[PDB]
Amino acid sequence: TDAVLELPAATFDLPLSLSGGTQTTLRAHAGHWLVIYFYPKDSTPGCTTEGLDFNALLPEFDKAGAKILGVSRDSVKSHDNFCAKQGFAFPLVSDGDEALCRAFDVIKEKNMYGKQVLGIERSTFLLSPEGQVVQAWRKVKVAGHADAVLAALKAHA
Ligand code: NA
Ligand code: NA
Image 1: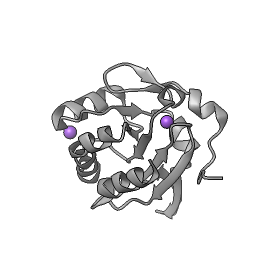
Image 2: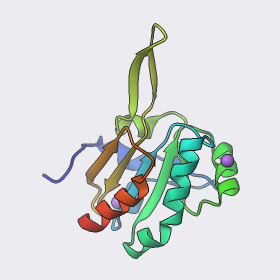
Image 3: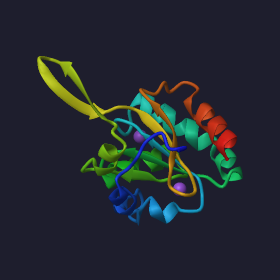
């Protein structure tokens, strides 16, 4: 009833490689809210702006017991460098095989260059303590986005 997106059951058990060398799974986050934001490329202007915006709001997400994960298909080492340079205090998922991206249907196609071109569409989701995807933002506008996600989280929580 309250889900806006249905994930395959296996999605919740995928090993997600994080910055810093550990793995997590979505099921491992049971019992608390989770914000998952997908972005197309480490260390680019929009992705850096977005990450810094979430980072600045961490204490507000903490107040709500929520955790955040950023996701792109960059490598663990790329993510480590990005986190260190920017000072991010939340993890980044290295979804190199786009398994998590496909589950959330964020790999979108565009007819461009006389080709069918597939890429990550900037998107964010709110996952409830019981693993339901209860809100989505697609084709995300970075300006104001982290603030809007925090507001929605508070309203849902
Ligand atoms: Na960087
Ligand atoms: Na959760």
